[PDB]
Amino acid sequence: NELVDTTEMYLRTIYDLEEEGVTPLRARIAERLDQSGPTVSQTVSRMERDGLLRVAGDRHLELTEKGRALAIAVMRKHRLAERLLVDVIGLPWEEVHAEACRWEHVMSEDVERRLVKVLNNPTTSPFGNPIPGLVELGVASENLYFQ
Amino acid sequence: NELVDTTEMYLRTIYDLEEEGVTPLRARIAERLDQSGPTVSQTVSRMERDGLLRVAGDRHLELTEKGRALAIAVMRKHRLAERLLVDVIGLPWEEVHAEACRWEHVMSEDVERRLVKVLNNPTTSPFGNPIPGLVELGVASENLYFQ
Ligand code: NI
Ligand code: NI
Ligand code: NI
Ligand code: NI
Figure (cartoon, rainbow over the protein chains, first blue to last red):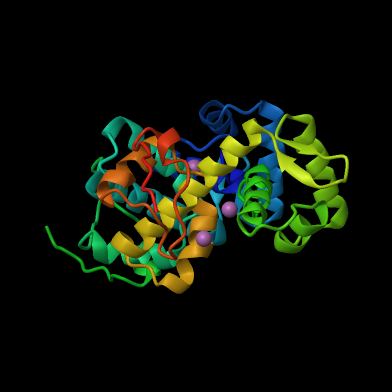
């Protein structure tokens, strides 16, 4: 299975769409994961059954609290993996996302906590984007900065 | 899929049994991968169909050369992963094999080659077993020391 974990990739794709300011719709998942329209619909309904998302009136997709927690954790592993691959392993930049897209599905939280120490409390991926879920991971808390 | 890559796990199980000097039999896979007798027997039949193994006249399994090259590459990834996990990431030794068991299925050859440099030309896993396939990786040559 090229996606490694299909469910986690539907979750991470919906999260991507949210960071991008794009409406999370099935058609976007089909495009980005190279799956047919009906396959996406069936996977999505199975995830709804599983309590990972809701399919709204207008057909837009919404992560549930359960689905959102899991999406965050995958994206956290993804960006920690990219940090590792660039900062420590020295994998060229143009190859790190593809690699991280596999590793995000197999990294334990224990490794993530080690990576947070080894990488010196990283807060962003190599590509500038914030790493989510660090509070839930147990390594950080959030302060407010007033502008 | 808890095996991450089922075929690769069958390959590496068969390979393990050959490292231990025991006979790789359909039965033996079922026990180590906690799989149905039928599931093993079926996957084994399927991998045979795909040029990965041959069932010998006495039922015992032997990897083709295609299958053996793949098993070595998985094992090589496994052991480099375990060395990364202990040496750089600092995950406890008690937990690295189970983590490496997943990561061995998603690591690219490019990452392996970087890991060889980063871990300073490793030749064994953290547990003293030789890393196979480093010549095929392209990073080493072999020489003989006469005893
Ligand atoms: Ni990425
Ligand atoms: Ni992925
Ligand atoms: Ni191991
Ligand atoms: Ni494995």
